[PDB]
Every structure is written in structure tokens, then in C-alpha cells.
Amino acid sequence: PIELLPETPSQTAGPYVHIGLALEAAGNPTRDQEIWNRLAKPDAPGEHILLLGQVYDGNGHLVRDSFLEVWQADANGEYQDAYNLENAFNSFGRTATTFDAGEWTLHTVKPGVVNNAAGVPMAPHINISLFARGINIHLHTRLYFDDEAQANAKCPVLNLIEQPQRRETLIAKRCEVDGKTAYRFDIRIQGEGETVFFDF
Amino acid sequence: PIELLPETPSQTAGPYVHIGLALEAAGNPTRDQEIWNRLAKPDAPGEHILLLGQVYDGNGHLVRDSFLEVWQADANGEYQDAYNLENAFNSFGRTATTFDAGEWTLHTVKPGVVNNAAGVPMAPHINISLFARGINIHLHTRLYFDDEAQANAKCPVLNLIEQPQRRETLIAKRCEVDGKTAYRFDIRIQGEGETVFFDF
Amino acid sequence: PIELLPETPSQTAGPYVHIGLALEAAGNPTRDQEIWNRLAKPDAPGEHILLLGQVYDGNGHLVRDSFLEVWQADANGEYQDAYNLENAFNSFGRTATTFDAGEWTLHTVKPGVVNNAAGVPMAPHINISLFARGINIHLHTRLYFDDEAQANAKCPVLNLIEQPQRRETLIAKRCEVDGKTAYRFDIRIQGEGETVFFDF
Amino acid sequence: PIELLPETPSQTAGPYVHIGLALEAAGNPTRDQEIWNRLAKPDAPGEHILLLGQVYDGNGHLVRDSFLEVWQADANGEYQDAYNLENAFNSFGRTATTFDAGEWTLHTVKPGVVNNAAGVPMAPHINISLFARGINIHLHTRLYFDDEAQANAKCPVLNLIEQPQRRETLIAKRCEVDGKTAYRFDIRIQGEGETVFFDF
Amino acid sequence: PAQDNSRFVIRDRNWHPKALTPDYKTSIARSPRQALVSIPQSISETTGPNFSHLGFGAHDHDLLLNFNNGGLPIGERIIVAGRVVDQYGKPVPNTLVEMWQANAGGRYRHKNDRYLAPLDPNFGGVGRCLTDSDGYYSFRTIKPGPYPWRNGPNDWRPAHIHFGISGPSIATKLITQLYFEGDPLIPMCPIVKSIANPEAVQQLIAKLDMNNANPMDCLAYRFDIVLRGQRKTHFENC
Amino acid sequence: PAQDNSRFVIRDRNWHPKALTPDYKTSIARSPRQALVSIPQSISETTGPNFSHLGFGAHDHDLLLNFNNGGLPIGERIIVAGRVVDQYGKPVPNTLVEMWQANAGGRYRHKNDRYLAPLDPNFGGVGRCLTDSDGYYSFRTIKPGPYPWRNGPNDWRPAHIHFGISGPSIATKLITQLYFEGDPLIPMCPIVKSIANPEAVQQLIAKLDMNNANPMDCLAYRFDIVLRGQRKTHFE
Amino acid sequence: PAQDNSRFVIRDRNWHPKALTPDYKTSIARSPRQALVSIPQSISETTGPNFSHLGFGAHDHDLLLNFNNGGLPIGERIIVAGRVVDQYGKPVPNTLVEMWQANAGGRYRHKNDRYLAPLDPNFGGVGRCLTDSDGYYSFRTIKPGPYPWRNGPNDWRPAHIHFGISGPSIATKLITQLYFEGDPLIPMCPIVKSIANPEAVQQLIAKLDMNNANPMDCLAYRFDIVLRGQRKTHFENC
Ligand SMILES: Oc1ccc(F)cc1O
Ligand SMILES: Oc1ccc(F)cc1O
Ligand SMILES: Oc1ccc(F)cc1O
Ligand SMILES: Oc1ccc(F)cc1O
Ligand SMILES: Oc1ccc(F)cc1O
Ligand SMILES: Oc1ccc(F)cc1O
Ligand SMILES: Oc1ccc(F)cc1O
Ligand SMILES: Oc1ccc(F)cc1O
Ligand SMILES: Oc1ccc(F)cc1O
Ligand SMILES: Oc1ccc(F)cc1O
Ligand SMILES: Oc1ccc(F)cc1O
Ligand SMILES: Oc1ccc(F)cc1O
Ligand SMILES: Oc1ccc(F)cc1O
Ligand SMILES: Oc1ccc(F)cc1O
Ligand SMILES: Oc1ccc(F)cc1O
Ligand SMILES: Oc1ccc(F)cc1O
Ligand SMILES: Oc1ccc(F)cc1O
Ligand SMILES: Oc1ccc(F)cc1O
Ligand SMILES: [Cl-]
Ligand SMILES: [Cl-]
Ligand SMILES: [Fe+3]
Ligand SMILES: [Fe+3]
Ligand SMILES: [Fe+3]
Ligand SMILES: [Fe+3]
Ligand code: NA
Ligand code: NA
């Protein structure tokens, strides 16, 4: 068969991932411009939301050194790929769990609906890649929203998960953090309530 | 790199381990001198204690053919390597679980404090090696005491266990058995409450 | 390690090198345009100079079939790479030793100062490549001028020659030839007074 | 044939040999006890002498980074092998050329006569090993004395040198340094007047 | 905004390390036990950030100068350079390459590093750059030292530099580790050996590159990176 | 206004012939005995002549017509063609390639050649051209004959053509010799064997190139030339 | 005093580097052109200094502590250890082993080192010790960096430590260089290649020795040294 060049193989981001990608969290000085967890300037269009979560290992213990990359459509359902700290909205961001509480946060807007390749609307979602010490190749998941139940039930991606109970692992819970609209999205890497992870 | 002679590889002690190392439990006559479960004659210095425990497999069932070897300091925190059935105290002994009840017992004294190689005091402990049918290489653990909370909190070995919840698995429970001070130390080889095992 | 394509290896220019690169000296007709030994037309800016020299082998005998290529800055210390027989000055030329006398000549201007890559001024110099029968790969040297003692003393190339006595081998001797300023630069390939040759 | 383990191969001592073996000369602090160039306390038995020399390469230039080890009998013809800074006399020492003048010095006594293995007396001599940048394996030589002409003419080691003219290269010249008895022993590694070097 | 105009060759997850590699002890509890759910590529997966407009500092790619507290870091001066291509051999231009590493003694500048070896007051250990229009990147740094870690009782990471590469989409994003030609620690490392195929491990080993060295100054190592092959869609929906 | 904006990969002087190769007798007295002195590259070394506006005659690259005295030269008609690239595989466009050779019988048109074989009145033995914008050059000539020479008592040069290539700087300038595929004289020649590594000698052997031949007219040989790798400065 | 009681196996001077090795440029003018003159062994050659009574400082063998100006040197912490035996395999006890090296960045603490790489204020670069009664020695140090030198235009020494070993006589005294397992600079170095036989070069390459490492602390390398075989005289003079 036809064989291409092989992809460079993944390795763990390791415990000190923050040195390279989360400088403040490492305990270090930061550079003039950093890629971080505020996707939306306060006047960006759409509904401003906080996202937060914790990450659990197979023993039920917090993964306090995890690093997350996120990619989402803006409120109008458009992916803004020209990354710039001066943009009103970036579709891309990064966040990391605090070492004390094991909690990550992201400041963004609720994404608009985008269609899949066959033209079928997907429910509003945030694409997440999870990296950490002990994770040899990053885990892909999606964060969907519990107040989009009608959309979620018809999502052609959620519908590829055979068991409805597993679909529930991808639905963030609406809540309030300091009085502001928020959604909590905990990830369970392994075991009871294990979060769905994707390959594509 | 430099490669030495390879160590002779381990194999399971198997179900009939008692033939060799626990003659009475096999149903067999014993020799004049046996190495067994009474580390302290009644007159030895220190707090005299009974130790007992059961061993559980991954399905929560008793491991009735367990064989345990123990190594501990005397009451003054000194290891006594000159093994002799005349001694008032020996630092080494052997025990086994009974085939009906699955319980092992030891008669000893509470060990004194011994420093690690860097000079830091370790909490009172008994070193245990666990052998059985289905165990390919013996498992190392330590038995600490729930009435030494302050010392356990500062033990530099216990502090190498990353999760506090796992440290609890090495703490034996003080009780009374026939008016005498005892400690129960159960070992769970696998699953919920899995006992910490060491490599060194 | 990383290995690139190998360079095509050198070979001697051989005794009949003049067929290709010095047509008149071979006894042959020349073409309309030839690359030869007059780098400066009479009207070019700078001090006009005649250069001449002989080439000696290891037994002190003349190398009568030497071919020399030269590369030098104009009087303002600029290298002129656009070769054209119309130019008042070209930075490049070629010469050869005559078969009877063994002497080569060049007609040029004294080059101006040019800085090395670290910004340090080099003394005025002409870069020379020497080719001949019995020379398997050409020899690189530099011709400096005895009336630039202060500059020669501080040249960062000359100062890479560990022994002062060897530096003297690269200093051409000012004289007069038919009332005109000249410099003699003899090259000794081998033995006593052996000319410094460079690798770069 | 019988082949033993191969000797570890030599390599050059390199330009920075002084770091390890001539600390002061490197420009560095010295340790409490150093192996150096004063073989004799002032009251040691025998005739106290200064030795000095320079070392020349094949181009007649000073080898300013050479390092020499010496081994000689005491005045009574005895080799004192128990090295100690408190000895009246050490048979062993080390010296190195100064970088400015290229000159080494040694303070010692004239050695007494020792016999070769066949019982034949050797002329008074100092065994020298010469090390330096560019010397891949150290060069062995002997320093004999020009005021021992009768002894030198009968030396069974000098007599192994086929040519009398080469024997002359090993004879140090008596002189006076600051009014004190001295012998100068220059070494020519290569070329005209090349010093005899030994294999044994 | 971004458009769905391409597809990315499916990953070989037996070429990459698997999730559960128990000799690397932390992977046991941080690996899923359920199968990954495969999904088709959509615009969500075939697009990603481009960092052309990120503001880079002058020394962001130069670890010899980007943590300057009075002098130069102590250590083996090296250029680390190479090309980012996809599996079809096509250069990946204007892509973000990030790296992070320990200092010459194997100490990380990170609050959680308990190793005794000292910090270097002139070394931070992070760099970033964008590949050029032909896919090439380069960094200047010091060669990191190996360093001991609490896995087995005497485990040591080989000298290594952590790399992150964005590529054209979130589908292509990769974190990996560069190792150094001839390092005898490489075949002993349980993190290296998370990769089951030794030919795959070979792809992570940077080669000494004398042609790229600066004489009297610094050595150089070449590390080329291959991201997932990108192709146009064909015969879809129709 | 030539500028210092590149560096050239350091030469491998065990790939090239060394200076002292005593079986090639004339090298004994014409080789240095002191080591070369290494120096860093400066604008003096990293620049050189560009010959784009040297005036070439119509036939400068065609030895069958550039010495025309009323007929064609006698001998094996051949095209000699190839590419000039650097060690990174980059083409070297607009560079000067010069060549010289003996005639079909091994006779050079040079006053110092004492070999008895006759001159060919319609053959001179010199050519020159510039590589094109993709790095390719081509000459038309006759295959030179082998040459006896006073080295050992029965030494013969294999058939060969001398080549000079300027390249982008004086640092890249090279003189070399082309030899012809299969010539049994090649492994016997002390000039060839000045190159210690037989894999380096292989790089000098031109291959018969039937694809570039003109049927019923001339054969062709391919000779590719690799000059030193050129790269930008970095971290200087 | 010393007595003549032994003979030493003749050196193989095609196993050792020869004097004239022109790729190592400085050897051209510092090599003899006349043959060495062979002489029989006498007491002058078969005796030499014993250093049992030399006063060693407490840290003389420990380069991590013997140039202490306020902290630890920066670099890869290593033990360098091994055994000194003769060609018959017999241990050489109570013999002086000296070593010297550059710091982690390839800078020597020597006035004549023109390399730009910085000095380490806590690293000197010299050590010494005596082999024990069984022939074993050991040092603690940091792994030296490679460093560039003016031979060819882009020549770099592999990482190396200079060793001097006295042995039982002046006939056995040796200076040599230790190199490190897997270093890709080794086959490129004209000083290494002064040794014509690559099997001889193998003897200078120290092997990674994990069995001798201190976990969470330092790696270890093993370097065994073989001096000339010593035997009793037999059938002499008679
Ligand atoms: O189709 C579904 C979508 C989301 C969810 F939580 C459950 C479902 O059955
Ligand atoms: O440090 C500890 C020690 C023993 C225990 F049971 C819990 C702990 O947190
Ligand atoms: O530095 C020098 C330059 C030229 C010369 F002839 C002698 C020198 O000592
Ligand atoms: O036998 C000799 C000894 C020393 C010397 F200088 C010359 C000789 O001929
Ligand atoms: O997903 C799995 C992968 C490997 C394994 F042994 C068990 C699993 O559940
Ligand atoms: O193309 C596909 C790939 C994976 C999947 F589960 C469904 C698809 O339609
Ligand atoms: O802000 C930083 C800049 C450069 C570096 F290597 C580390 C930092 O924390
Ligand atoms: O999976 C492996 C990868 C590299 C290696 F050297 C050994 C392995 O078992
Ligand atoms: O940007 C791209 C889009 C489609 C493709 F096949 C390759 C690309 O590099
Ligand atoms: O002086 C020399 C002697 C022998 C050799 F191979 C090269 C030299 O430069
Ligand atoms: O500074 C230098 C000196 C000599 C050399 F060959 C190269 C250099 O970079
Ligand atoms: O002027 C010439 C022209 C062509 C040739 F082959 C030789 C010459 O001497
Ligand atoms: O150096 C050589 C080159 C080519 C060959 F065929 C033999 C040799 O000895
Ligand atoms: O002693 C010598 C060794 C090698 C050589 F080429 C010439 C010599 O004179
Ligand atoms: O044994 C001997 C060895 C070398 C020599 F020149 C003479 C000898 O008698
Ligand atoms: O006196 C010294 C002591 C230790 C060292 F590494 C270097 C010195 O110069
Ligand atoms: O003499 C040599 C020694 C080691 C090596 F790798 C190559 C050599 O030519
Ligand atoms: O001291 C010694 C004397 C003679 C011998 F053969 C071996 C020795 O180690
Ligand atoms: Cl925040
Ligand atoms: Cl003195
Ligand atoms: Fe790491
Ligand atoms: Fe059995
Ligand atoms: Fe010819
Ligand atoms: Fe060195
Ligand atoms: Na594993
Ligand atoms: Na050599």
C-alpha cells in the first residue's frame, strides 16, 4: 500500500509543561504577549460566559497539572483563526489547572452553531485538547451546554456516541460564579463517569 | 552501558509454600528449630503487642494461602540481625494466613524510631514482604501504627506517597484482643483501598 | 550526524592549465574577451600599482607553470563582483608565471580597508589562490603591503597566525619598476620561509 | 601468540595541562600540597644545582606550554620513591615552561651513579618525560652533565646511540644562574640538533 | 474567518505511544479505559489558530539572551533547527513552534521541581518562534542535562527538549520531545518506551549538524517534524 | 557592493586529495609542510566574481566549431552536460564553467606538450559557458584520448577533461577533472588516486547518457558538480 | 629506597597514537623526525614515585565541592569511577590518578582559554585521588561540554576529561583522555583519530554505569585503565 512519511510521535507534556505554555503558573516572569484564557474582550459580541472545571484521574484524585487548549466558534458561528491579542474575540485559548484547587477557568462567549461536513447543524460546542503529565498523547473532547438540550439531542457528533449515558459526560452544567453565568465541565479521565474522548 | 550479571528472576511461592517455610500449616511435622511468628519472648523490653490481619484479592475475597515475612527494629530502634531462638528478641519472623479464617498473627514489640539515610526520623514501622500463589514477585509494604499520628505525619517514607488517602492504607488499627494491646493490619492487593506497595 | 551531498573533489590543474585559463601563455590564439591580469584601467580611482612575484618549490626552484587567481577590494574598500571588461576596475583577475623567468605580474590599485565579520578592520590585502601541476587542491593566501605596518600589526587575520615570523611571509615589498610603484610578493610553497596558506 | 589486555592508549596532555598538574601556571589557586620543581630541601645531601631549559619545535620556535616530569637518584645513587613534601629529597618532580620566556627550572642535587641491569655503571643522569599540546605520547629523554665526560663516554645507555653527534644532544651545559651552579638542557623536538628520545 | 477546505490523514495510534504504558507509572491512572470515539472531520477539527499576528519579542527564540540577568547561561551552546513538513512532504510555513527545557544540570525553572541541582540565574528555559515561509525554524539554547525522577527507584530522563507545534489545524497540533543523538539514556527511559516501535523513537532523535554550527561559538542539532498530511476534499456529498 | 550575507560549509580535506601524495611525484616538492591556518569567513572569502556580462562567442561551448580551420575535428563526438548544485542540492545558476582537454589522440595544443601524437588542425581544446538559470551547462566536444606522462615509467592519464567552476564566491571556486565511465585506466592513475576515498573518485566519473545523445550524430556524458553548501548566517 | 625487581611489557606504539598525525595540526612541528632509540630496562625506568604519603585534601576527588565559592557548579552531576589494572589483569593499588576538564559549557579555568563560554564561579576543574587497595578510584564532577578549537575551521573536541595515571614506575606513567559513550563528536575529532586503530579508541570511551549512580542525585560513568604489564625478571645475567 501507499505509505506516507510517518507523523512525529507524541510524548507527554510532562509536569513542567507550564514553563513553555503557562509561564505565570510555573512561577515565572511572562513575556509581553501570552496565549491564555481570556478569549473575549468585554465588548465582544455574544453572551459572555465563564467556563470552569476540574480534571480527575482513575482514582478520583485531582489532576493538578493539566493544561487545556480550546477552539470554538464565535457567537456568530465563525471560527476566528487569525490569532491576535488585540482581537475582540479569539477562537483559540489555553488554560491550566491551579495546583491548590485543581481548577481551570476560561472567559469566553457562548459559541454559535456550525454545520458538519454534510451540512447538518452541530450543537454549540467548545473543542478541548487535554495535556498533562502521564498523558502520552493529548485527549480530545467537546464541551456542550445543558441549556441547549434540543440542539444536543440532534447533534450529529453527539449521536455518534452509542450510549446515551456517555453523551451526558460532555454536557457542561450551567451555574453561577460570583453571580455571573458560568458552566462547569469536569473531565474524568478514567473509570466511573469517564468522559468521552474522540479520535479524528 | 555497564551491565552486571542478571539477578535470578523471581517466581511465585505457589500454594504449597508451607511445605518449605511453614511446616505445621502444611499439615506436616516440624523440625527442632523453626522460624515463626513470635519475635519477642515475654521478658523482652518494649510494649508487647499482638498483630493480626487478613489479605484480600481484587474481588474482595480472602487470600488464604498468604505467607508474610517481617523485619522490624527492637523497642530501642535497633535492628537485630543475629537470628537465634534463644534471643529475647529477633527483628525477623514469618507468619501465614490460616486456611479456614484467612488470618495471620504476630507476637512482637512496638518498634522504636529509626532514621532514614539522610538522618530524618521515620515513624515506627514493621517491614512486610508478602508471598502467595499468584504473586510472581513478593510485594513490599510497611505497617505503621494509628497511635503514632504525629510521627506518621512527618515520616519521610509516608510522605513519598503522593496521595494522603493512600497513606491511610499503611496505618494499622489499635484494638484489644483478650485484654492485650493489638493492631489489625489488613492488606488489599488490588482495587478499592489497595495497599501501597514499595519498590526499593 | 547530518551529512550533506559531498563536494566534488579537487584535482590538480596540471601543466597544460594555460590551454583553458591562460590561452596566450599556452602558445594559442585568444578569444575576443579574456579574463587576465589588468584589474584597473589607467583612469580608475586609487593608487595604481604593479605587483609581481615568483613561486618556489620545496627545493628552492621556480614553479614556472603557476596560475594565480586574485580577488581584492577597490580603493574604497568595496568588492566589485560584476565582472565586465568595460569596467574601469574589476575585483578579480588571473595571472601566470612565464616559462623562462617564472615571474607573474598584475596591474591593479591598492585595495582599501574592509572589515571582518565582527566589524574589525583588516589591513589592505589581495586574496590569492594558487594552482599548478603538482598542487592537488589550490592554496589560499593573502598579499599584504609593507607600507601598512600599523594596519598589519592590528589585522585580525594576520593575528590568527601564531608566530610573527610567519606573518612576515604575507608582506609584499615596496619597490619601483620603471619609475612606477611596485610590490614584490614571492611565494614559497614549502620549506624555509614557507608562505602561510589559509583554510576557510 | 599470547595477547594480553591492551594498554590504554595515550593522548596529548593538551594546552591546558596546567589545570591538572601545574595549577599556579594555569593562573589558578593551589592546594595545600603540590608536586613541583624543588626536589631538594636546602640541607639535603649532595651538590645543590639548578637545572633549566627551553623546548623547541621543528620550526625553531619555543614550546611555551610544555610540562616535564623528572626522576633521578639522590646524591648517594638511591631512588627515593616514597614521595613526601617533608622529605629532604624527592627523586620525583614536575616543572613547566613559563609562557613568556618558555623556560622551565628545577632545583635539585646532582644524582649519584647507578648501575644498569647487567651491573655496568651509568653516567649521572636525570630521566625526563616531556608532555605538551601536540605531543600525542610523551617523549622520554635523559639529561647527563658536561662535567662528567669520563663517565658519559663509558655509559652503556649513551653507547646505544649509534652516532656520537646525537649523544651530544643529551649533555647539559654547566653554567651559572644568579651566581649558582646550574646546567642548561635545551630540548629540540624536531629537526636540526634533534634531541635523542628513548623507548623502553 | 476559517473555512473547511482540507482533510488530515488519520493518525496511526500504534505509531504514537498508547495511553496505557504502565512502566511510565503516572500513565496508569491518567489513561482512559474506554475506547476513543471516532468522528468525521468537520470545520471544528480541520481549522485552528494561525499565529502570524502574535507579537514575538526579539529574543523569544534565543534562550541564551531571553532570560538575561547579567551574563550568559552556563552550558553547551547549541542551535536547534529544522523543518516542519506534513506527511506528503509539504512545508508547513508560519506555524508556531514552542519549546521548553531544563538547564545544563537538569534543573527546571519551575516551582514544582524538587531536584537539588542549581538554577542558572541566566537561563529560563522557554522559547518560541514561527516557521518561515519554507517551513524552517530555529532556536539557540544550551543542551539540557538529564535528570532523575520518581518513577522507578533509579530512573533518569535522557537530555531532552519539549516541543509543541500548532500546524494548520487543531487536528495537527502535537506535543513531543526531542532527544539527542547517541544518548545512552534513551533506550532505558519508560517515557521514550511509551512508543512501542523503536523506528518511531528514531524520529525523535535530533542529529548533530556540523554544517549548521557556528565555529568557535556553538554546535547545532537538526530536528525535523512531520505533521499529519493535509489534502483537499474529494468526492464528498456529491 | 558585493555583500557578506552567507557562509559556506567547511571543506572536508580528507575527501579532497591531500597536498602530499607522493606517487604523484610533482606533489612532493609542491605541497606545504606547515599546516594550513584556519580563518573565519569574511566578506573577502564569501564573495567573488559574477561573470554574467563576460562576452561569450557563439561557439565558446562548442569545441567542434570553435577551432575551425576548414573541417571537423577527428574523434568521438560527444556532448558533456550536467548540473552545478551546492551541497544542500541548490542549483548554482549563471556560474562560469571552463574546460580544457587533449584531442582524440591525447595531444594537447600547448607548446610544452612533447607527446608524439599529432595535433588535429580543427581542434583547439578549450571551452567555456555559464550555467543557465536552473544550474545546467553543456559543451560539445570530442572524447579526449589517454596521455602518457613522465611520472612512473609507464603511467598514462585516463581520458579526461579539466574543469574550472567559479560558483558564488572565491570560497567555492574549484578545479577538478572529469573521467569517463568504465575507463580501465582510472584505478591505475596516481592523480586520480591522490583522492584517498574511492567513493570520492566515483564523483568524478561521467556517466554515458544515451537519453541526451543526438542519434546518428553524437553521444553524451553527464557530469554533475557539487560546490560547497551555502547558507545564511545565524546568531552572529 | 626503590629497587629494580620487575620488567614492564614493551609498548605497542601502533596501538598508541603515533607522534606525526598531521590532521592534528600542532603535532606536525612537535613530533620527532628521528627514530626513538630503544634501551633495556634498568632501575632508572622500572622504578617511580609512590604517592601514598602525599597529603590529600578532603575534597580533592570531588569537583562539586573543591572549588566552593558559595554554591554548586551548574552541570550534569556525575561520578567517574573505575579500576586501574595492568595488562595481566592485576590491580594497581595506591596509585595516583589525576584529572582535569572544562566546565559544563566547555570553558576551561585557564588563562590561555580564549573560548567565550562563561566560567562557572563554583567549578575549578581539577581532581586527584589514589586508587584503593583493590585498584579502584572515583571522582565526582560535572560532565564537561565540548569545545571548539583552532585546528580546522570547524573542529570541536568531544566532551572529555584529561587523565594522568602514575602506576608503579616511570615506564607505566600515562596521560590520556576519557570520552563519553555515544558522543557523536568522537569519530570526527583529529585528536581521537591520532589513534589509528578504532578498537584502541574504544578503550577511551567511558560507559554509562547506572548501577553506580546515586538516585535523585548523580549519574555515573565507568572508566577502567590498563597500564603496562608488570612481571618479575627471569633468567637475567645468570
Ligand atoms: O442524545 C443525547 C444528547 C445529550 C445527552 F446528555 C443525552 C443524550 O441521549
Ligand atoms: O501524612 C499522612 C500519614 C498517614 C495518613 F493516614 C494520612 C496522611 O495524610
Ligand atoms: O603582527 C605582524 C604582522 C606582520 C608582520 F610581518 C609581523 C608581525 O608580527
Ligand atoms: O660517547 C659519547 C658520549 C657523550 C657525547 F657527547 C659524545 C660521545 O661520543
Ligand atoms: O482501553 C483499554 C486499553 C487497554 C487495556 F488493557 C484495557 C482497556 O480498557
Ligand atoms: O466518516 C466517519 C468517520 C467516523 C464515524 F464514526 C462516522 C463517520 O461518518
Ligand atoms: O518570561 C520568560 C522569558 C524567557 C524564559 F526563558 C523564561 C521566562 O519565564
Ligand atoms: O518501545 C521501545 C522503544 C525504543 C526502545 F529502545 C525500546 C523499546 O521497547
Ligand atoms: O492550506 C491547505 C489547504 C489544502 C491542502 F491540501 C493543503 C494546504 O496546505
Ligand atoms: O609536514 C608534514 C609532514 C607530513 C605530512 F603528511 C604533512 C605535513 O604537513
Ligand atoms: O575565530 C576563529 C578563528 C579561526 C577559525 F578558523 C575560525 C574562527 O571562527
Ligand atoms: O582561441 C582559441 C579558441 C578555441 C580553442 F579551442 C582554443 C583557442 O586557443
Ligand atoms: O585512493 C584511491 C582512489 C581510487 C581507487 F580506485 C583506488 C585508490 O587507492
Ligand atoms: O620519523 C618519521 C616518521 C614519519 C615520517 F613520515 C617521517 C619521519 O622522519
Ligand atoms: O635489551 C636491549 C634492548 C634494546 C637495546 F637497544 C639493547 C638491549 O640490550
Ligand atoms: O586550587 C584548586 C582546587 C580545586 C580546583 F578544581 C582548582 C584549583 O585551582
Ligand atoms: O583512527 C580512527 C580512530 C577512530 C575512528 F572513528 C576513525 C579513525 O580513523
Ligand atoms: O610490585 C611488583 C613487582 C613484581 C611484579 F611482577 C608485580 C608487582 O606488582
Ligand atoms: Cl482567571
Ligand atoms: Cl622556580
Ligand atoms: Fe522534561
Ligand atoms: Fe510447585
Ligand atoms: Fe590533462
Ligand atoms: Fe581538553
Ligand atoms: Na510500559
Ligand atoms: Na592525522
Image (tube, coloured by chain):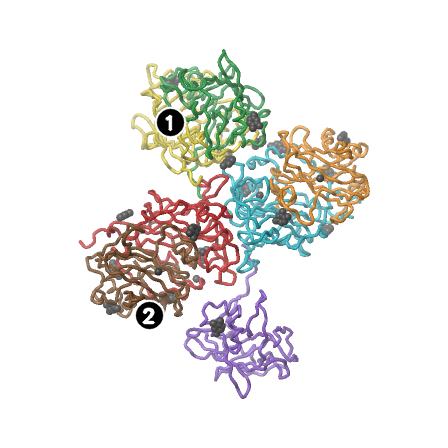
Chain colours: A brown, B purple, C green, D orange, E red, F yellow, G cyan
Indicate left or right for A142 with E224 as reference: left
Which residue is label 2 attached to?
A193
Chain letter of disc 2? A
Where's residue D57, x and y in %?
A: 63, 32
State ligand 6's quadrant. Answer: bottom left
Q: Residues within 10 Å of mark 2 (few under 14, many from 20)?
A: few
Please report contact status of discs 2 and 1: CB closer than 8 Å, yes or no.
no
Quadrant in which residue F70 is drawn: top left
- State the CA–CA distance, disc 2 to disc 1: 72 Å
Q: Nearer the viewer, residue D87 or G94?
A: D87
Compared with residue F96, is residue B38 higher up or lower down, i.e. above or below? below
Q: At numbered mark 1, what does the secondary structure look like: helix, strand or loop?
A: loop
Where's residue F181, x and y in %?
A: 40, 32
Compared with residue G47, is residue F139 higher up or lower down, i.e. above or below? above
Three-letter amino acid code of the residue under disc 1: Asn
Compared with residue F159, is residue B145 higher up or lower down, i.e. above or below? below
Indicate left or right for B19 with F89 as reference: right
Can residue D107 be seen by looking at this rendering? yes
Three-letter amino acid code of the residue under disc 2: Gly
Where's residue A85, x and y in %?
A: 32, 51
Q: How many labels does the image show?
A: 2
Q: Which mark is residue F50?
A: 1
Where's residue B68, x and y in %?
A: 53, 76
Farthest bottom residue in view = B178
Q: Is mark 2 within 8 Å of ligand 1?
A: no
Can residue E202 be seen by looking at this rendering? no
Indicate left or right for E85 with C120 as reference: left
Q: At numbered mark 2, what does the secondary structure look like: helix, strand or loop?
A: loop
